[PDB]
Image (cartoon, rainbow, N blue to C red):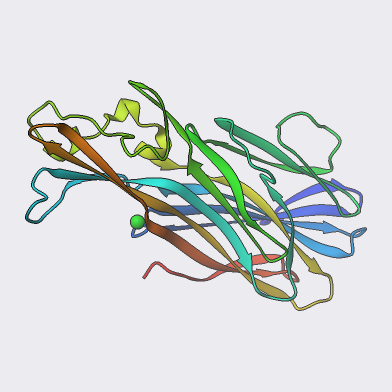
Length: 287
Ligand SMILES: [Cl-]
């Protein structure tokens, strides 16, 4: 037990903490996942609090459009939504909580999942408001210009979508669905495609760089049902394309292809062993 990260959380209860880090250079994703087993002699179920962190590259790019008639057209590919989800199919496991639980539109998201001996979970959309829990886990992330929604939630799966919402632009606030979002008339000489789009200082981090997720869901398992369960964690993005064409007579013309690339996700299959309190990577879609 000395080589295992174990926290005593009160009489007859402790948390066994495991981690896995799994990255894909192909998908531009890192999953830094924490898996905390709640061991409580006064709770008839096993529980695994799964905290999903890491990185999802924006995969934003600016390029020329090849072909006849497209000589004056440039393309910006950028992430309209980041996808984070966890799914199970084994009858022996279900999801009993998830954070965030509701739509949240604030630039900063900071929430807490608390546990009290006897199988009692509670959540709050804030950090620091409570010192009554036997154990707690928090989530924290920034999503400037984006909003978080629970796209799917049920006893077997949860999916969050962190979606483009409203942006600060030189001309004022613009909707994520405005076809002229990020478009501009070019001025300089070098690397022309980049110049048809808003400079980096106008692109918020979720467009320019990527997203650092922080989400939780708790897996529930009846003590005495089968030893292991598999589940998949998916991180990725949906990309839009904004096309900008410079017309000699009328200026810059923009068109958007919304949902241009959907579900560009890195999926990792894990196994939890409820008896040995271990986690293993079983498979993934790196190739
Ligand atoms: Cl991609």
